[PDB]
Amino acid sequence: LWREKINLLNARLAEAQTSEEQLQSQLDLQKKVVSDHMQRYLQV
Amino acid sequence: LDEAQTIESELDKQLRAANKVTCVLDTELTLARAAERKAQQTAQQGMKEEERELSASHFPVVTLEQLPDIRDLERQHERGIQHEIERVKAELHRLNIELT
Amino acid sequence: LWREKINLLNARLAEAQTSEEQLQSQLDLQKKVVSDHMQRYLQVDSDASVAKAKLDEAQTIESELDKQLRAANKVTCVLDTELTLARAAERKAQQTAQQGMKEEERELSASHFPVVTLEQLPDIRDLERQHERGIQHEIERVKAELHRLNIELT
Image 1 (cartoon, helix red, strand yellow):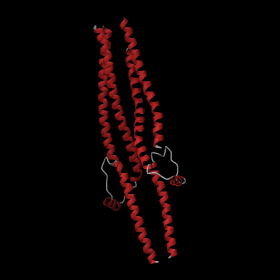
Image 2 (cartoon, chains in turn yellow, green, brown):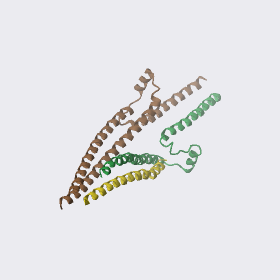
Image 3 (tube, chains in turn cyan, blue, green):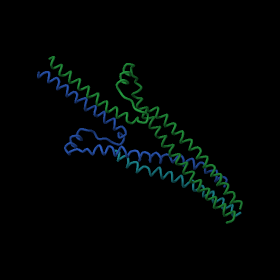
Image 4 (cartoon, one colour):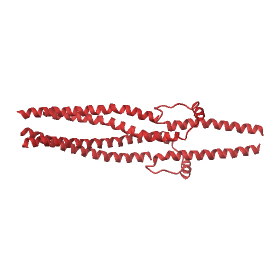
C-alpha cells in the first residue's frame, strides 16, 4: 500500500508542477509585455 | 508600460499560491518511502506458501485510505483475534474443571 | 509531548517566516534595481548597452532572489505541513486523553510506566507496544496461576 501511495504521488505531482510552470509562463509573459512596451519607447 | 509593470503583482501572488501544492506532493512522495521499506523488510522474514494461504484466507485486505491508520486498525484486528483466543482458553479452563 | 512539539514547530515556522519576509524585501529591492536599469535604458558599450546588460543582470539576480524566496516558502510550507500533522495527531490522541484519569490511577501509572523525551515522541508507541506485551504476559501468567489454584480448590 505504501508502494501504491508512492506511485499515486508520482502520478499526481505533475499536475501541480504543470500549474506552477503555467503561472511561471504567465509571469514571464507579463515581463514580455513590459519589454515590448519599453522597446516601443526605445524607438521614440 | 506602467500598467504592465503593475499587473505583475497578481501573477506573482498566484504563483506563490500555486507553489504549495508541489511542495506538499514532494514532501509526501519523499515521506512514504521509509514506511514502505520498513514494512517490506518486516515482510522479508518470509512465509511458506501454506502459511501465506492460512494467513490470507481469514485476514482482511487493506487499501490506500486505511493505510495511514493501518498501524492501528491492525492492532484492532489483533484485539479481535485475542479476544476470542481468550475465550478458547476459558473453554479449556472449563473443560479442565469438568475433567478433574 | 505533541503540544510541546507543536510549539517547537511553531517556533521553527516563525523562523522560516522571518526569513521569508526579508527575502521578499530583497526581491523588492532587486525589482527596484530592475526598474532603475529599465528607466536608464529608456533614457539613453554605450551607456544604453550597459543599461540593457545590467537590466538583464538585475532580472537574473531578481530570479535568483525569487528562487531563494521560493526555497524559503518551501521550508515554511514543509514546517506548516509538519505542524498541521502534529495538530491532527495531537487531536487524535486528545480523543482518548480527554477522558481524564483519577488521581490514584495517575499515581500508579506514573510510578509504573516510563516517559519519553520531547523529540523522541514517535518512540512512545514502541513503549506502548512493549508494555502492552509485558502487561499481557503478566495478566495471562496470573490468570494461569489462578487457574491452577482454582483446580486445586476443586
